[PDB]
Image (spheres, helix red, strand yellow):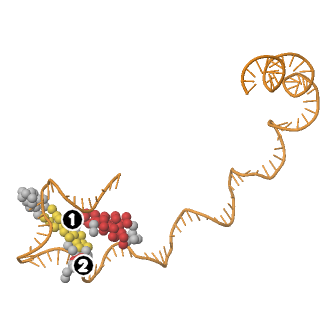
Amino acid sequence: MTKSELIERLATQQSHIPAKTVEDAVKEMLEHMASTLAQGERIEIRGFGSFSLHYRAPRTGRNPKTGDKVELEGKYVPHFKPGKELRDRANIYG
DNA sequence: GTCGGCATAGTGACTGCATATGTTGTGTTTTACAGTATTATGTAGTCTGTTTTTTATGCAAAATCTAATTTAATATATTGATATTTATATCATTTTACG
């Protein structure tokens, strides 16, 4: 399921909703979630999950191909935490 | 049947009678527009009452929107073996992107 296939299956089910409307809606939601995480704000969707931002202290990296040294500026990285409903439904085991 | 000599055979030139054609002159009959007058025309200049349209509120109907509020959901905080992501960047493959 890609970004396009996602809009396709959502437009097929929603007949009373223009296909073009669903196409833009999906693109605006993803862009809104990507912009929020950029501003430094978290995301919390009850049932789905919750996006966060974890800090990464600056450390002297090392080229994994050769083994040299490379500086690494301190930055933040997105982190998703599956919700309760998401885990239980995605968990096929016990 | 052709070739040789007056007779055929329509068409063209020639001359004057015979008559339609070209002018000149008198005279009747009717067309054709100018100028004032008569009156029902079509729009004009307004008034008036009915029909039409803009206008100023009025209110039951409709449900979102904001604040009070409770609770599942989220975060802190342990502890430590085990599993996943991680720095760089040239090759390789999938998906976006416009014509």
Q: Quadrant of residue B32?
A: top right
Residue at image x 6%, y 58%? A67
Q: Chain of mark 1?
A: A
Disc number at residue A89? 2
* Chain to which the residue tagged by mark 2 belongs: A
Kind of residue sitting beneath label 1: Gly
The answer to which image quadrant residue B76 occupies is: bottom left
> Could one spot residue A84 in this view of the protein?
no
Q: Which mark is residue A40?
A: 1
Mark 1 lies on a secondary structure that is loop
Residue B97 image point, x, y percent: 30, 57
User: In the image, is B23 to the left or to the right of A91?
Assistant: right
The amino acid type found where label 2 is placed reads: Arg
Q: Is residue B47 above or below residue B36?
A: below
Q: Identify the residue at horizontal 33%, vertical 70% (top origin).
A: A9
Residue A82 visible, this angle: yes
Can you give x and y, in whole percent of width and height, for residue B71 in the image? 24, 83
Residue A49 drawn at (x, y percent) = 23, 73
User: Would residue A65 be found to the left or right of residue B17 on screen?
Assistant: left
Label whose residue precedes the other's in the sequence (2 or 1): 1
Q: Residue at x 19, y 80 (%)?
A: A93
Image quarter of the N terminus of chain A: bottom left
